[PDB]
Each structure stands twice: as structure tokens, then as C-alpha cells.
Image: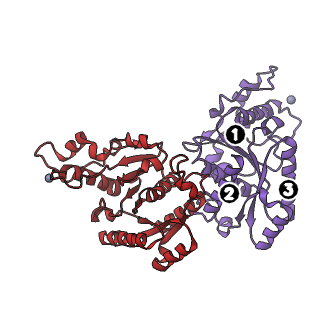
Chain colours: A purple, B red
């Protein structure tokens, strides 16, 4: 399956993504985990040290490959065929999970970054449309890496939000952008829930059938989110709850 | 960890074992799954066809190896060193799970089977005491393959029973034999629960802290237990419940 996980906050949302990826390794022989959020470290939540994650060259820094896929001076290519060279664009964390880091885009400094952006786009296209393997791509609230073309291949867009007015609004906007792009299913995972009043707030603004699951706030999560990996470990209190969320996802996608 | 799963019934108990093994593959790089119950097919519940499971030569039929480990005519050896040749005594089901089948012992036909029994015993000893890898051994209510020596290496003995007087008695006897052998922890998994009255019966005869988990009887389990694998699949209704049982086990063992 092809999954997209989006939201603000950063680590919180990335924590859910890493959790699903790890659980997914039991059902798939290979998973492409794509870090498309420069503000959080997907590799870290997947068990690597922040250092090991950053030692993986990001897509944006593969100049030799970018030259080879878009042309060398003058020679322009708007549709780079990179689906065959994917394994050179990241590192296997283990026998099943292959991590790719997009890297951050240069917002806009009067310089030309067309070749770079074309290269990133071609990799995202390859992963979602050409590769058969499972893909989980972690991204920001703007989901700017998805296009109408790749959106048709997405099995589900998961918006991760916190139980408050502003975060709920963010999620509804994610849902708006995804629908506009043509994504078939959008579902929510509510994170950092502290009290029941907050759960009632969620139920008031969001359809319950659209809620994949609820993850309670963890005190051992604010003072321990960089040692014993994450919520996918069998010792973590969210372990079982996370598998329920995964089962609902699997059933939803078919 | 080193686990032993015992009970009557056969498939029911073997179903729990296979479930734990599959879930365990996420936490361990290699697991020795040992079918020590000739009445049920552990490999089948682990995803193989009954045919593929039976094409794996059982310990009892490795005459060449048995000769090489106990002597050849006259030459007797009561303590065969077979911990180094384990990978020749089974088949890898996949990249992590290695299946070994004990085969059935000749109850007693006036023939000498000392060499055979010594060989089986040496393999069980090697797995529990010498190998570092995780081991899950499925066995009958008599747990006759365990000895006081190997019992010291067992992290937990799991007795699987049904909610009725006779099955409860069976489990208490399993607990008796295990304690006598010196096994440190015995825990229960109650299977095929049909109603709440039965749950009350369990609570009446067994300490609740000793109960790892309860598995409801499945109607799609009586008419579907040889097609879509088992309870470890993400589409199975017992999926989440099984992970809760696994977490309690992990926490118990430490
Ligand atoms: Zn340009
Ligand atoms: Zn003899």
C-alpha cells in the first residue's frame, strides 16, 4: 500500500508514521520510508540515532545523480526516469525498511532550482506510481510533494492532529487539499490526548467513522522520546493501541 | 527468550504458539520454532501448507545424523554435541523463523530406541541452554521433552486451556509438572471462550494475575483455520488481543 502521513507539530506526526512503518514490516517484504518533513527526523523515530539519519545523503544533495537525470548544462529533462535507481537514493535501516530523505527545498533565493525540484518530483512519482513495494511518506501540513498524478496512487492520507481548535482546523485544511488533489480517503489519528473533554471536542468537530484511532498523551513521552525508540516497541504503552489503528487502516484499504 | 507452550486439544494450543512466534519475529532476528506435538501441525499454523510442513524431515528420521551423534554400533554417546549442527535439523520458513519437527516417539515396541531419544534430548538441550536465539517449543500436556536441566532456561511455560472443569484440571496438572521440573513461571491463555459464565468459571478456579489473556471462540475459526493462516494476521479479529497477550508476556519476562 501507499500511505501519506501529514500534520504540523513535527515529531508527534512523525512518531505515528514511524509506528505504522515498523508494524508494516510484518506484512511487507520491503517498505520505502520517505522523510518529506525537514522539521522532524523520521529515521530517529524508526530507531536510528539522529546522527545515523543525517549521515544518509538527502535527495537534494545528489548533484551527480541530478545532473544525470535532468541534463548537464542546457540539456533539460522535465520527466526523469529514476524508478530504476531508487536504491541509490537512501539506505536500508535493516533487511526491510529503506529510508529516503528529501531534504529541504530552497524556499526562493533568486537562484534556479528547477533541476533539483524536478529530480525530487521524479522520485516521488516513481515511488507511488511505478514501484510495487509499500511506501509511507511523512510530510508537512502542506503536502506539497503530492501531485494530482501521484495522488491517484495514494491508498490513504492520514492527518495527525491534537485535540484543540487550531489543530482541528489544520487537519480540515489537510483534508481539503487532499480532496482537491484527488486523494480518495483521508482519515485521522488524534494524538496527545490529555483528558476526556478533549475527546468530546474531537467528536464534536470530526465524524467518528473518519477517526482511525486516539493516542493518549504520554508523560514518559515528553521526557523520553530519544532513547527507547518509540510507540512500536512491545514495551511501549501505546503498542497495542497502535496495532488497533493499523488493523483499521488495513481493513479500510482492503 | 525461551518459551514453552503446552496443552491438550492440539490445534487450539498450537494456534497460540504460532501466533506468539509470528509476533516475536518483530523483536528477534531469529526464532527456533519447535513442533514437539505430533498431534498438531505447527508449520501449518505458521503459514505453511500441511504438505510443506511434512516435507521437513523430523528429528526422529535423521538416522545418518543420529549415528554420527550417538555412535555407530556399540559406540555409545549419552551426551551428543549437536548445538553446532542445528541448522541441518529443520528448514527456514522465511528469513527469521526456523522450524524443527521432533516427530513421534515409538511409545514402546520391545525395540531399542535409546539412540533416537538421546538425539532428540540433545537437540532440545542445545536449543534451550546453548543457543542464544529465541525459542518457542509447542508441546503436549505431558511436557515430556523438558528436563530439570533445560527447565532452568525456560523463561515461561504457557498453559493453554478451555473454560471448563476438565480443561482447567489439565492446566493445573501442567502447572504441577512444570513446578516440579523447576520452571520459574507458569501463565495461562484461555482459549475458545463462548460466554461470560465461562469467564466467571475461570476467575473462580484460577488467579487472575496468572492469566496472560483470554481468546474468544471464533465462528470463522471452526470453518476457516486452514486458508488465511491464523490469529497473527492483521485481518484476524484476535490480532490486537494477541498483541496484548504478547506485551504482558514481554513485561513478565523482562
Ligand atoms: Zn529554472
Ligand atoms: Zn536401548
Q: Earlier in the sequence, mark 2 or mark 1?
A: 1
In front of the other: label 2 or label 1?
A: 2
Residue sitting nearer the eye, A98 or B48: B48
- Give a yes or no on whether discs 1 and 3 share a subunit: yes
C-alpha separation, residue under disc 2 versus residue under disc 1: 30 Å
Q: Where is residue B235 shown, x and y percent of the image?
A: 62, 52
Which residue does the numbered mark 2 point to in the structure image? A245
- Give a yes or no on whether discs 2 and 1 share a subunit: yes
Which residue does the numbered mark 1 point to in the structure image? A58
Q: Where is residue A177 shown, x and y percent of the image?
A: 86, 46
Q: Are marks 2 and 1 in contact (CB under 8 Å)?
A: no
Q: Earlier in the sequence, mark 3 or mark 2?
A: 3
> In the visual, does A200 lie left or right of B133?
right
Q: Label 1: few (<14), some or many (≥20) within 10 Å?
A: some
Q: Label 2: few (<14), some or many (≥20) within 10 Å?
A: some
Secondary-structure class at tag 3: helix
Residue farthest to the top, as pictured: A75
Report which quarter residue A148 is drawn in. top right
Q: Residue at x 87, y 52 (%)?
A: A173
In front of the other: label 1 or label 3?
A: 3
Residue A137 versus residue B217 in the image, above or below: above
Report which quarter residue B168 is drawn in. bottom left
Q: Residue at x 46, y 76 (%)?
A: B206
Q: Earlier in the sequence, mark 1 or mark 3?
A: 1
In front of the other: label 3 or label 2?
A: 2
Q: Can residue B81 be seen in this snapshot?
A: yes
C-alpha separation, residue under disc 3 versus residue under disc 2: 21 Å
Q: Where is residue A129 shown, x and y percent of the image?
A: 73, 34
Q: Can residue B29 be seen in this snapshot?
A: no
Which residue does the numbered mark 3 point to in the structure image? A170
Q: Residue at x 54, y 53 (%)?
A: B232
Amino acid at each position: 500500500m501507499k500511505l501519506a502521513v501529514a500534520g504540523k507539530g513535527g515529531v508527534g506526526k512523525t512518531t505515528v508514521a514511524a509506528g505504522l512503518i515498523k508494524i508494516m514490516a510484518s506484512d511487507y517484504d520491503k517498505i520505502y520510508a520517505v522523510d518529506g518533513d525537514p522539521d522532524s527526523c523520521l529515521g530517529q523515530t524508526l530507531g536510528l540515532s539522529i546522527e545515523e539519519a543525517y549521515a544518509i545523503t538527502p535527495l537534494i544533495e545528489m548533484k551527480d545523480e541530478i545532473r544525470e537525470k535532468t541534463g548537464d548544462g542546457g540539456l533539460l529533462i522535465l520527466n526523469p526516469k529514476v524508478d530504476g535507481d531508487l536504491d541509490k537514493y537512501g539506505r536500508y535501516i535493516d533487511d526491510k525498511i529503506f529510508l529516503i530523505r528529501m531534504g529541504e527545498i530552497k524556499k526562493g533565493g533568486s537562484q534556479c532550482y528547477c533541476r533539483e525540484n524536478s529530480f525530487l518530483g521524479s522520485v516521488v512519482s516513481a515511488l507511488f506510481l511505478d514501484k510495487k513495494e509499500a511506501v509511507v511518506m511523512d510530510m508537512g501540513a502542506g503536502i506539497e510533494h503530492l501531485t494530482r498524478g501521484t495522488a491517484k496512487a495514494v491508498d490513504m492520507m492520514i492527518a495527525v492532529i491534537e485535540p484543540n481548535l487550531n489543530s482541528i482546523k489544520t487537519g480540515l485544511n489537510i483534508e481539503k487539499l487532499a480532496g482537491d488533489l484527488g486523494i480518495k480517503k483521508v482519515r485521522y489519528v488524534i494524538n496527545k490526548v490529555r483528558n476526556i473533554k478533549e475527546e468530546k471536542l474531537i467528536k464534536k468537530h470530526l465524524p467518528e467513522d473518519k477517526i482511525l484511532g486516539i493516542i493518549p498523551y504520554n508523560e514518559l513521552f515528553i521526557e523520553l522520546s530519544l532513547k527507547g525508540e518509540e510507540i512500536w516497541q512491545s514495551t511501549n504503552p501505546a503498542f497495542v493501541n497502535l496495532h488497533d489503528i493499523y488493523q483499521k487502516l488495513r481493513l479500510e484499504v482492503g
